[PDB]
Length: 237
Length: 300
Image (cartoon, rainbow over all chains, first blue to last red; front, top):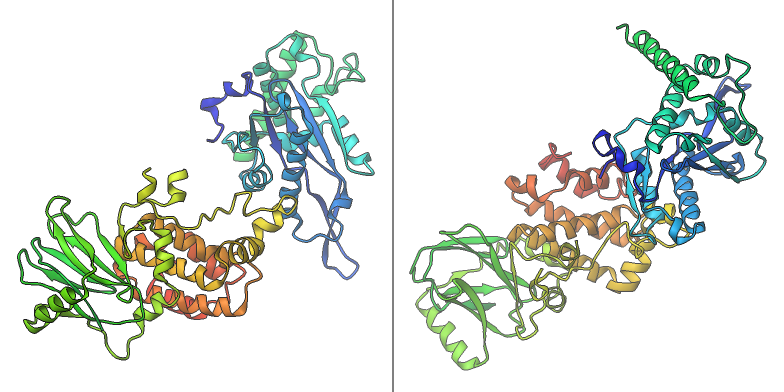
């Protein structure tokens, strides 16, 4: 059944699993027409498919050409997501295929179940967790490869950089969800916290800065402060 | 007009014949049901006064043989049996009629209700859903499970309704996942009508049989099958015009006959709301929508 606070350690066991987040697949800017009507212009999007144990990110870039001449795009976007996740699973060697796929949005369950009928032993699960994977496009290197794409493309990343050399996958996931939650709540402030000290850089082959263990504790505290502040404002409490 | 004689009535029981029902007292001199209309299937059904659990009964067609009911005190039920001796049977029926120990099938001349509920129902199709090949009549009860319910446990006692499953490889062509899931026309027209049922008459016959088992026996798997067969049509953008007009008539009479007090357990809110207000066919079932809105507006 649903993945929640009660069965959280299951994310870091030795059963291959992927999170699928479709919130950045269909992206638009809303604008006025010459006649003063409203129209949308699609921009490139992405499927966010993540192994929470290893940090492997399968970023399938959704180029605006896939929407051309299609109707009901927010509906189609769920089916295209499920088509591409199904294609990803079929492309993996059997021993690398997931035993479970956790969708961040319940509207993905039927599309993904129907595309995965050929894989009756892969469990398709919702989650009660409110995961901040929508903020993936606040990670500058991910935003850059999506916006520059001129055709459909899959790009592979490790969203944990080299953190698993020093920390467990539980701790890495908690750091990732804290970073993304901060970026989602107040992007400008979160990016200021991450880049404020010019001496700590991002390696060419990394997404995040090269913090020491002590610098990560300071950063994580600055992100928690950012989130609580913002919350008191949202709710006047 | 045919007759189903009863050897006796040793236990107090409510006896159904089609949409009619009669209370019989323990050892009441009751010897059966006469003037049964030829040309239709019929169902004779029972609910014991001392155990209002297990409604059970028999589907039959008096054109296929001479049938009677006899209580079995070992198995504790009224059983249907065939009398192969025509002269013995004619002589039993004539004696019971002369002594007026039989209830008359109480059909009003104007009243097409039973025809309307059984228009496409054939005894030869019933005998394939309910497998007991040594009898020409078919036993159904409240508890019998469907082949589909069993997959998700005695195979000989199952209702072999056609399995319908909207998230199955049978329902969904590789490469047409979104198309086939959102528009079930290929599943309805190619897989089910052309493939399995061969024609709309056999599909409607099964739909009508499932409804009648749901209504007469409170058979839950039958209710599931009735709703699945409605939803498969309503969820298809491409349905022949004759089938939609016929389905509207079928469902109108079903909704008309349903006891008002059983709408809560016999009608699925999701299916009916989706079929009447959201589906491709939301505007194709005028008669059904009008009777549902006037008889069961709470469900909607």
